Structure formats: structure tokens, C-alpha cells
Image (cartoon, coloured by chain):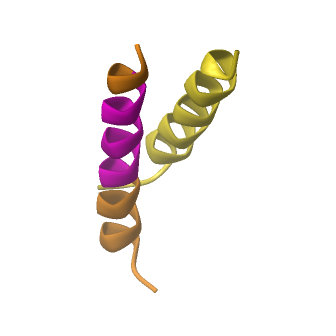
Chain colours: A yellow, B orange
Amino acid sequence: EXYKEXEDXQERXRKXRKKXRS
Amino acid sequence: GNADEXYKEXEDXQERXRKXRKKXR
């Protein structure tokens, strides 16, 4: 039931990381 | 603050979430 929301939360952090330099 | 620290902390929390998700699955 909250599977799609946790995947999206994970995806949003991935998007935040992609924009940052190492 | 620091960019290198933010990046590492985000990598770590993403991984903790991934493991919590794998455990729920």
C-alpha cells in the first residue's frame, strides 16, 4: 500500500543526488 | 555544511531505505 510512496521517496533522493557534484 | 558530506549522507540514507524496502518485499 505504501510501496509506491517509498519507491518515490527513494527516487526523489536519487534525483537530488544526481544534481550534486561528488 | 559541506557538499561531499551531503552526498555521502544521501547515498547512505538511500541505501538504508533500499534495505528497508527489500525487507518489506
Residue that appears at 34% across and 21% down: B22
Along the horizontal axis of the image, is A2 left or right of A21? Answer: right
Q: Residue furthest bottom?
A: B1
The rendered magenta stretch, by its main secondary structure, is classed as helix
Residue that appears at 29% across and 60% down: B8
- Where does residue A14 sit, x and y in percent of width and height? 48, 36
Along the horizontal axis of the image, is A11 left or right of B15? Answer: right
In the rendered structure, does residue B14 fall within the stretch colored magenta? yes
Residue B19: image quadrant is top left
The magenta stretch is B11-21
Residue that appears at 39% across and 80% down: B2
In the rendered structure, does residue A9 fall within the stretch colored magenta? no
Q: Is residue A8 above or below residue A22?
A: above
Task: Identify which residue, B15 or A12, lies in the foreground.
Answer: B15
- Where does residue A4 sit, x and y in percent of width and height? 66, 16
Along the horizontal axis of the image, is B16 left or right of A1? Answer: left
Task: Identify which residue, B17 or B23, lies in the foreground.
Answer: B23
Task: Identify which residue, A13 or A6, lies in the foreground.
Answer: A6
All told, the count of numbered labels is 0
Q: Is residue B2 above or below residue B4?
A: below
Along the horizontal axis of the image, is A16 left or right of A21? Answer: right
- Where does residue A21 sit, x and y in percent of width and height? 37, 55
Screen quadrant of the C terminus of chain B: top left
- Where does residue B16 sit, x and y in percent of width and height? 33, 44
Q: Is residue B11 above or below residue B7?
A: above
Residue A15: image quadrant is top right
Residue that appears at 51% across and 45% down: A19
